[PDB]
Image: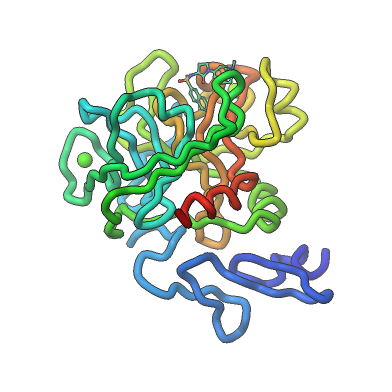
Length: 52
Length: 234
Ligand SMILES: CN(C)[C@H]1CCc2cc(N3CC[C@H](NS(=O)(=O)c4ccc5cc(Cl)ccc5c4)C3=O)ccc21
Ligand SMILES: [Ca+2]
Ligand SMILES: [Mg+2]
């Protein structure tokens, strides 16, 4: 297990392998955090989250 | 849903319910965004005229979060066939936008490659609906959810009396009395990843409900992500 095969490449959501490195991205309604791994909701009621 | 548990407050917020002229649910759907609902193409024959209700957990009481929406356009996959239920998918555009709130939120659409290697390889998915609680019973008045194991493609093909196409996958139990059932059709099959739920399937069909040696058959959403994207862009 390497890159995206190793614990989802440490990404919160989508993991892609580009030029032999990990590239993380997020679903619509989320923005990639400054660490390039976590996904932060851009507004209220982000997709895929149970409410309250 | 046969077996499983009730969806508790806020737990299944992406659940939609297709209701006929009698304000009765006949199929489920998944909220994709403020304007779009994902459902099974075969549901588009169960009633002549229908609306979509969201935010409902108990069809007997008014819990305050319910909202009925009229459909503006029906986007049925043109390759859907009643013969085998291949391409059992449709997207509905609503006339008015859904207002998200407690019990009303969309499920995420994943990317194809990542979902196939990371979501569909998880142990389980979650199915939900107001469908029958036994094969011969009546529709549930309560929204239910059920954890369903992903089933080996080979085992699934061996269990089935009918063709499992590339647009289908199997989930559930060999012998355990838990499965989706009549009325759950078109509803959500979602997969949890780090506390975020992604749409992975659409309740499609099965040889009865919770039968021994039979599994629940779901439309493989990952095969239609590009199709969904186009359907939502118009
Ligand atoms: C021969 N072709 C037509 C194949 C493809 C479509 C299909 C459907 C059925 N049946 C038989 C009855 C059952 N209806 S049901 O309401 O009990 C139902 C409907 C949807 C389900 C969905 C899941 Cl995931 C599991 C069980 C389900 C059960 C149901 O869906 C049997 C065979 C075939
Ligand atoms: Ca209600
Ligand atoms: Mg079974």
